Image 1 (cartoon, each protein chain N blue to C red):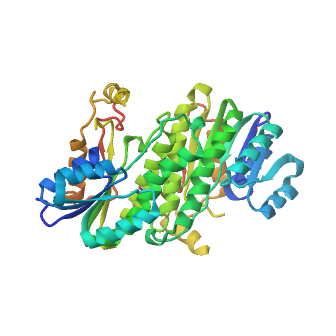
Image 2 (cartoon, rainbow over the protein chains, first blue to last red; image 1 turned 135 degrees about the vertical axis):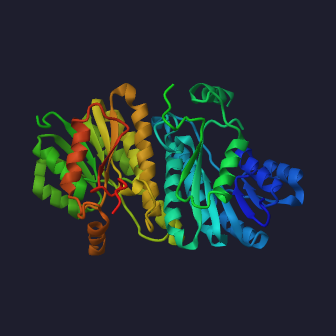
Length: 237
Length: 238
């Protein structure tokens, strides 16, 4: 059901990215994926072999983005889905935030994402799509996550603008908003307690939403899709 | 009564909406410290106001100058009731023409600068006080040519929400005004007359009224947004 489809998954070595990669592969799609850490990239090549193209790349490094562009072109040539997954956070009250921690989070979550898209967009087929992995924190106020929340909100706005500008090329741009996803232990339990559905989501649940938007939501652009157990949906208690 | 005893800082207060807000603050009897980048604009504020306002050249994007502003504010004012962030630069271009330079400077002023200005100035805000951000209709939806600007403003709005949540124990409210087309080249004002549901641009003063309402009258409002856009961001068809 993914026959002939070519996909790029930025940050596909772990969790939700890897779950998306797995589904893409089982469906018969050609996949290129990237990842910051090299133990992950090696682990991937172990698991998939020549079934997927794994590539070590730092989304924050604009030079490495250039390498990525060449790689993608020489490898896939044209793509149907560009899925932007990568994201980092540093949990600290707003008055403890330093310039470095501020810079780090925006460099990966927003800037790197923006320029990775800018570089890869000319490869995307007409009818293809971009899917951003946002967060439930892209709306509302979450103490200790000022920078991360803001970086994701910026990302969602980019998705909206890209959706508008890419209309004439018939390219859809959407986002998924994961809540607590079990992919640190004190965080899963926080997720169990505050999430209305009283559990964490799975990486596969997030992947199903990514691929729905990618391939089945053919009349959906500029939209957001919550995978958050209701957390961002204002469900009381 | 009206704002006597009130102390305000207006970041980007030498022009447009910031200036309109300053004018009302002064008119109401508040103590005002404003900042701007253009020396000329400042000198004009000085001619108009004199010792009534403390005007400062300060680069919101420069963290060193933000430090200096922190000391100057703490010195001239001591404690403030309102911090109004009215900063905004934009560069119009399709997303595939944005240079790292364009990207960086828009985010440096609109988002990073605002964040650290707030981080440095917040200890001066007393209980019952508030922060008001000037966002934009562009902070939601997709507006071709304004990818960086919209994204930078959407980030600002998210900061507002997190600040609102974190500042709760201190009794400091945090909100945002979202202006649409505000008449402050002519091809832009004309577009505003055409696509705005109310078929006109707004005024700086209209933006100022919403800012000061949020500042001093909306005492049970935090984490919120108030549109001053003639309905533009309100999904009114035709």
